[PDB]
């Protein structure tokens, strides 16, 4: 899962 | 404990491991809109903190507690369940604030505070607001709040709006059509194409977009954190009745959220709307399984139903119909497994948005 | 079971959930170098499959079992622990191969096979070869292999070589130095800079690079799948003695791997080398927190030690020194959580 | 003597030995902007010099005195404390001006002029204007100035402006990080990394740059040489409030200066601005040990404090903060020991 | 004290201020030939250090003492006069060697050692070897050496050789001719042209060169540090008799130096010769006021006399003559005020060095 | 004086 690996998304 | 009961252990392990990384703290801290707004909300409402007792739920590195300390808080209890609680302790000592910030490692549902507090601060917003189910921990913490106490943030607004995006919709079948092949290295894959289509449509899209793809004003579902209780978030029913401002195909619903810090001096807003500067929450879009044709003036009505699950997320159920023609569509999505589609380019406006000749405006 | 003993439960759930998604099968399948090399190795060595009994460990969509069937296998047991076993079954039926390919759901450590097999096939390679620890499942499956049975792939070679990449180093160093600030919104973060550096450089870097950044010929660690026992992979010691071909700063060690399919007709190689076409494995580079200065002709010596952990990966220990000067660099990396720079 | 009291002996020996070399006089003289601007400022204001008595403070080779003589000065006392005074005397004789230019060897604070003067001329500006502390000698010489007398230059404007230059920062930061190594030939140097950073960023950087790197309009501090006192330059407090015009990282403050010759006929300016032709003064930049992030519209406020020391320079203290975020930077720099970066 | 007697206060202030900068320690430490050779000389002669008492004269950051510790020294007394003694103490603590390295701040001529030592180590070489006059402090430190003690380095060799470099010589007058103009902004500067020429010719030139500019095999003047006394370096007379290998105009003398670490196991050599990799000492060249024509086979004879001064340097007197013609030249130079001419370019060989056609050797 | 300013020369 993507939310299990990264709950918060990356911002540049 | 309330947390262990509603959370699967597998989800909790990966969840708090992720937040034990300093790199993830940095990503959040470097979100200027998010960190600066929290600072402005706290320092500009200094009376809400001066000589007060504070609780910071999920303090992470403790940055929000340092803001409360800058505002004059007498005592701050910073609770963090990840291993980040150790790094927050190191920062409390290095900043000579051991007398005013107490780091309590553990889950806010399981720790004990020596006393009640005047104000709770936290940053419990996931993408689409509700992901991670931290809002329930934030509300659970009100058991430590004095009768007259405040909450920073105080309320949250979730905004929903129908959008048109032919490329996003068609992309789901372009990706699935990998399986519509009679001889992949000699193997006919076509029997799985429908399963691939189903898999993509269960994913919300975490992205940004141009506001001109929205076809109606948003509807807002507000959560007053001072009044709401934990159970109010277990099942979130959001009815909508969109008055179409544009005619076209509606491919789904777009989501964003705002929060307000209602202080004694002023109210400060933190918005993740597509009209505002981008945040690390971006925006979220859920496609319909089939597009709905709507004319300007029609009403697109339906429900967005969010059902909390034990993986610290929600199962999303959307049903919508255009009242004037009865055309209906639906979809079921897993909020925990979105597709991160952001690329870094400026979002393009939908075709057919020029009402004056672009050639006449080359030399405006 | 052997698997549940060596694997934490939370890691196994996420692991097999990941491989249940068709999108993740598509990603691997569409790696044309990987998939085409496997097919060519099997079909060219059709004698190793003609009328043979086959075991496909971690068949996923079943693609490799279809290749063995194309090569003439009589029966293929395709073991898959994720929910992808369902989709593989659909493909076996839709391709009218129910008489030759038998999907067996479950972990190869826990299922029961009706008979022994003549050859085992699998794609158990993670990035840097050993991630995911599926090589142990591949070796564990030899309990079903006839005495002189074969294995596809037959051997695996891990290559390591020192590299210089000032740009990569400064990227990771600059990120970590965010925690050097004395006044982030008025907060002194500097007491965490050491922890930051330790964390960021604990991440191996997955991307591709040009061979020109390598400062010495690589050393090779070989796993012979025909001979190895799964216990051999719990602790992997790789000593190295690099003869520096260029002067400059050694910023870390680069990793990649080749596997060989040693068939009766021919041996076929699948390579993830930085000189070969890109695969979904890319290459892997472990950075030193502080680079070592070396002169051409010096020897960079040390040990790369891989200790398997219960999250289906390895804790990597790299100790290296420039022998002529005694400059040493020690680093610990988490192979499970790399930084994808590509 | 006033000079010996505010100057350490080991600093004065080296200082005046430096200016005894003809090569150093050539370096200043060949600066065409400096020398040409001084000449035109004097000749165009010839009424300020015609039949007047002139004092040249630190005449060096005597070039400024020859300009005053060209303008019609009746008598010029050229004071010079280095052995350059002997070479200036040779030039006065070889140019047949012994009747009008009198070279007086020694420090202007320790010599005796036979009479008072109508105008003082000098080139006392150092890097960032104040280095060398010769401005105090220039002001000290006002003891010999007549009530209605003038000063050339008349005023000095030092300008400050925040800049962004990631390349410059990373050069200095990388040098200091040499002392982060844990195994230099097997020796752990890391315990000195903090001390190294303090040392490298204590050095102001002397070179030139494009105006593009400036993030806000400059702030100006003015010294009026006609009315300022020697003691006014012992402690110089320069408060600043910069309205940021661009977003990005503020890596420090950039410094330059203009001087004005306020003559009776016209006013002539000599500028070391980064938008003007290069002079041997270049420009000066004081780096923050850690940059400050600012947004367009923010305000960068603080104070630049210069405290004169007995080595003929200043200890610079720069404190700055982004008001909107409270992000602060504090730095101490030694103006005497800059890093000359111009390649 | 012996140091204060022979040194002017102003010179000592500038001198030790310079060596208090970490940046200057880095410059020396990053000279790989210099630091690497010292490490090898010490570690490969481990028997000269194993369980021995060591004195490190002018230890700076202490790097040489750490090498002695790596070789097995029981006790090391690291004397340093600049404020770098503080930074060295920090390094001794951080490296957990306080029991084996004792940093003594102050001048080796003025401090007290609790005992005598078996071996003295130091890096007392300035450019042209003798500049800075630290060799005398190195020899002075022998008052702490046991009767049969060793010294690292043990001997020093200064090499002299005549060179031809028309460009270097002519550049002196090109620079001075700035003053040979009759109207510099209306001022005749010509009367100072001779003074400018004098000023440039008093400066030795520090840079590197191609060995083919040398016109004769070098002459070597050796200092044996085991035997030499402080007073031997107050007046250094170096006679020379050069037998010309090439015909041309002799423009001056080039200087470089080597040192030898004569250990029990081996002798390690550190060379700054123009045939070796560049060091931070480079090489040093002193011009003649007038060039001397010599033909191959002639003898160029004369004396190089170094007279120590109270500014920690030497006044250089060079006299030379071509015996076959009697043509003589001389010059007086200040070793303390050299001109740093190094640009970073590879030195070009003297013209007229091609004995075969370069065009025929294109493509090889 | 160049020697008073820098006894030891800079090596790039
Ligand atoms: N212990 C185990 N037992 C059975 N399958 C396993 C396993 N460990 C990993 N796997 C499976 O092995 C597969 C490896 S990746 C898929 C490879 C497949 N042959 C293809 O080319 O498409 C995954 O599907 C994973 O679910
Ligand atoms: N206190 C003092 N008294 C007299 N001369 C001084 C002095 N302090 C510095 N100087 C001299 O002033 C000179 C400054 S450089 C200016 C040289 C000359 N006026 C020109 O414009 O070309 C130096 O040569 C220095 O020796
Ligand atoms: C979105 C940010 C969440 C932060 O709060 C922490 N956190 C999550 N859940 C809890 C509970 N129950 N108690 C304490 N802290 C919690 C996350 O680790 C993150 O820092
Ligand atoms: C080339 C310089 C070497 C180091 O030696 C130090 N040093 C010079 N002279 C002395 C005396 N007399 N005592 C102690 N240390 C001395 C220099 O400071 C430099 O670090």
Image: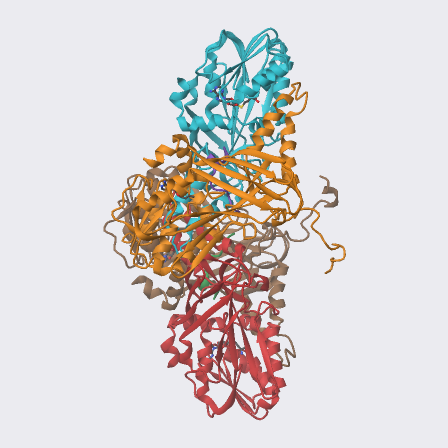
Chain colours: A green, B brown, C red, D cyan, E orange, F purple
Residue at coordinates 53% horizontally, 51% vertically from top-left?
B218
Q: Is residue E31 left or right of residue E174?
A: left
Q: Is residue B139 left or right of residue B170?
A: left
| Farthest left residue in view | B114
Rendered location of residue D199, percent (x, y): 42, 40
Please say if C34 is above or below E353.
below
Q: Quadrant of the C terminus of chain E?
A: bottom right
Please say if D194 is above or below C323.
above
Q: Foreground residue, B319 or D152? A: D152
Q: Can you see residue B29?
A: no
Q: Foreground residue, E306 or E138? A: E306
Rendered location of residue E209, percent (x, y): 60, 46
Q: Can you see residue D90?
A: yes
Q: Foreground residue, D54 or E143? A: E143
Please state the total of marks drawn on the protein image. 0
Q: Is residue B199 left or right of residue E295?
A: left
Please say if C327 is above or below C305.
above
Q: Is residue C84 left or right of residue E312?
A: right
Q: Foreground residue, E124 or C30? A: E124
| Farthest front residue in view | E324
Please say if B339 is above or below D31.
below
Residue at coordinates 62% horizontally, 72% vertically from top-left?
B178
Rendered location of residue B215, percent (x, y): 59, 53
Q: Quadrant of the N terminus of chain E?
A: top left
Rendered location of residue E279, percent (x, y): 51, 49
């Amino acid at each position: 899962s993507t939310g299990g690996k990264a709950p918060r998304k990356q911002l540049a | 404990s309330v947390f262990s009961e509603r959370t699967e252990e597998s989800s909790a392990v990966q969840y708090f491991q992720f937040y034990g990384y300093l790199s993830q703290q940095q990503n959040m801290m470097q979100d200027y809109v998010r960190t600066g707004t929290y600072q402005r909300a706290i320092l500009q409402n200094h009376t809400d903190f001066k000589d007060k007792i504070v609780l910071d739920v999920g303090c992470g590195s403790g940055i929000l507690s340092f803001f409360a300390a800058q505002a004059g808080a007498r005592k701050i209890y910073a609770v963090e369940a990840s291993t980040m609680a150790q790094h927050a302790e190191v920062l409390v000592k290095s900043n000579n604030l051991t007398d005013r910030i107490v780091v309590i490692p553990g889950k806010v549902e399981e720790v004990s505070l020596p006393e009640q507090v005047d104000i709770i601060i936290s940053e419990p917003m996931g993408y689409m607001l509700f992901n991670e189910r931290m809002l329930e921990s934030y509300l659970h913490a009100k058991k430590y709040l004095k009768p007259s106490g405040n909450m920073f943030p105080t309320i949250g607004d979730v905004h929903l709006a129908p959008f048109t995006d032919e490329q996003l919709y068609m992309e789901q079948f372009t990706k699935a059509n990998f399986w519509y092949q009679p001889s992949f290295h000699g193997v006919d894959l076509s029997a799985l194409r429908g399963a691939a289509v189903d898999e993509y449509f269960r994913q919300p899209v975490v992205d940004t977009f141009d506001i001109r793809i929205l076809m109606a004003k948003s509807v807002k579902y507000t959560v007053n954190f001072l009044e709401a209780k934990e159970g109010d978030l277990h099942r979130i029913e959001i009815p909508f009745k969109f008055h179409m401002l544009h005619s076209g195909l509606v491919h789904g619903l777009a989501f964003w959220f705002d929060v307000a810090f209602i202080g004694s001096i002023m109210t400060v807003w933190l918005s993740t709307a597509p009209t505002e500067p981008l945040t690390h929450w971006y925006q979220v879009r859920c496609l319909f399984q089939s597009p709905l044709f709507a004319k300007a003036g029609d009403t697109l009505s339906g429900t967005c139903l969010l059902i909390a699950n034990k993986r610290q997320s929600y199962d999303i159920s959307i049903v919508a119909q255009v009242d004037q023609t009865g055309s209906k569509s639906s979809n079921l999505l897993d909020l925990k497994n979105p597709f991160f589609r952001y690329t870094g380019t400026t979002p393009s406006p939908p075709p057919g948005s020029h009402y004056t000749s672009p050639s006449e405006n080359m030399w405006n």
